[PDB]
Image: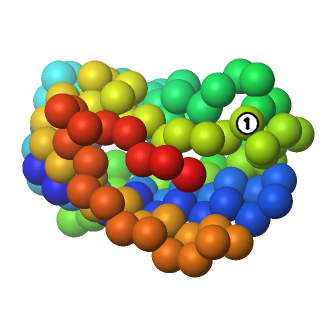
Amino acid sequence: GVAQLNVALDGKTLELELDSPAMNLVGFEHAASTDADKAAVAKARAQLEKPLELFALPVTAGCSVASQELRSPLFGDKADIHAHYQLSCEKPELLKLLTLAEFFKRFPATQKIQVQLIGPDGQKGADLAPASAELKL
């Protein structure tokens, strides 16, 4: 139950890249057949489309979404989910702490998240888990 997250904080710009097996987010590795499959896909799509909620960005930072991409056949019009987010924060000084607590609540099949961070300070790695879901930005 292992996802990657790449974070990049340069000034106003916050970039988030999630790479996860479909299993963690949707509950299965096939394309969507049954009603129960189509409803799990739609629940995951709706959640991944609200990144300020899923990554619990603090409202005080003034974060807004400039772009977001879901790359998977599950989310196209016709075995890995990629989710790319470009955010812009009016007060990025207030981004002190990234919490994946909400990601773990909304996708409880995710047991561990490997985070890479890149910032004016350099590169930083951490393994996050429901137990310790926080990372100093």
Based on the displayed image, in which of its 4 quarters is residue 34 positioned?
A: top left
Across and down, in percent, residue 66 comes to 78, 49
Up-down relation of residue 135 to residue 121 (above or below): above
User: Is residue 76 in view from this perspective?
Assistant: no
How packed is label 1: few (under 14 Cα within 10 Å), some, or many (20 or more)? Answer: some
| Residue at image coords 37%, 60% | 115
Across and down, in percent, residue 52 comes to 61, 31
| Residue at image coords 47%, 55% | 83
| Residue at image coords 71%, 22% | 59
Secondary structure beneath disc 1? helix
**Residue 33 left/right relative to 100:** left
Viewer-nearest residue: 51 or 31: 51
Across and down, in percent, residue 16 comes to 55, 56
Q: Amino acid at mark 1?
A: Leu
**Residue 65 left/right relative to 8:** right
Q: Residue furthest right?
A: 90
Viewer-nearest residue: 90 or 73: 90
User: Is residue 129 in view from this perspective?
Assistant: yes
Viewer-nearest residue: 44 or 89: 89
Q: Residue furthest bottom?
A: 122
Based on the displayed image, in which of its 4 quarters is residue 28 positioned?
A: top left
**Residue 118 left/right relative to 79:** right
**Residue 95 left/right relative to 53:** right
Up-down relation of residue 37 to residue 2 (above or below): above
Scheme by which the image is coloured: rainbow
Across and down, in percent, residue 39 comes to 29, 23
Up-down relation of residue 52 to residue 8 (above or below): above
What residue is disc 1 on? 94
| Residue at image coords 53%, 61% | 7
